[PDB]
Image 1: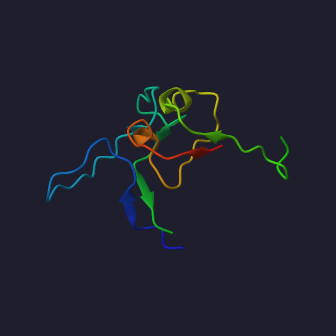
Image 2: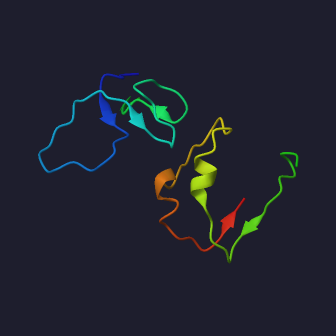
Length: 50
Length: 50
């Protein structure tokens, strides 16, 4: 398994054309705020290809 | 019900509030495979099999 290539599964809004997002900030996927901490409906935005 | 005789409920001719179901913290697993959880309140479907 080559897991070195990653894609942004989760983001709040769509990008502009020729826009790059390298910010590793947490995403809030639910009603509960995450406060930078993983948990229930708190996921890392960057997931790797298997 | 048991899993060999799983109960099938037909959800139709009604308006469905998926935000209450999604914002509930009792659920340990909420995984969608054909739609998005945040767009369930925007899309429309013919019927739902539960």
